[PDB]
Amino acid sequence: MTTTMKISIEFLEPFRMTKWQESTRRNKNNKEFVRGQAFARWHRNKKDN
RNA sequence: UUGAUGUCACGGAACCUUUGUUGUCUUCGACAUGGGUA
Image 1 (tube, protein in one colour):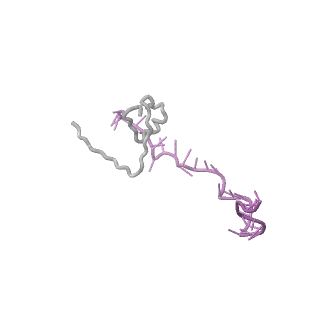
Image 2 (tube, protein in one colour):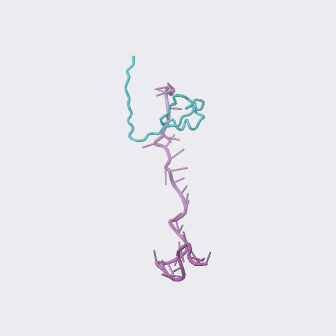
Image 3 (cartoon, protein in one colour):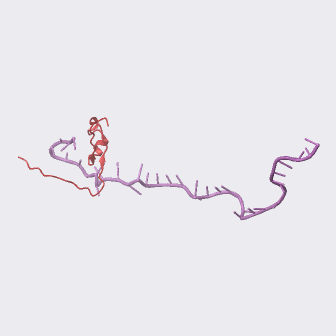
């Protein structure tokens, strides 16, 4: 038993997004991935392009 | 397209340094033209 709460966020400013990286590099040892953890994330449909 | 008992990323000024500068009197006299004649 759960209740779903529809959430929308309206940005009043340009928001920051983090650069895409390989799933091999999405760990605490990669500085760039950790530094961008508070930003938005880009999703790739396919890893190649 | 996240994972969860732990995110100061509003935690970080694209910032700092380079002269569109230099040189020149709005001045002034000899031609122009191609043959023609035998």
